[PDB]
Length: 49
Length: 49
Image (cartoon, rainbow over all chains, first blue to last red; front, side, top):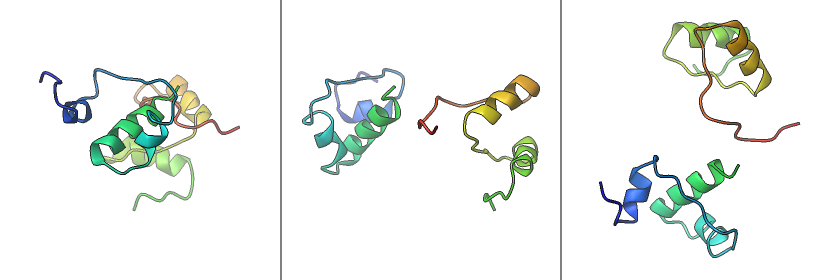
């Protein structure tokens, strides 16, 4: 689907994503347990290389 | 059920059943260079020396 929802990023795995290494984008996504943000942290840390 | 004492019994289990075995990196390279019925999935998820 068109990815206008933030849950659509958790739905797909084709369109990959990254962020600048700030703790607001990395540490805040790591903790502060939201399930779609858990998916975001899982795809960021699993594709950290 | 999925806990394997050895390496090659896991090789027979991934060869026979609907089972996925986890090896580190180099034995994966050895069995993919050796056996043409097996393949690896994804990238290296850690950096063990």
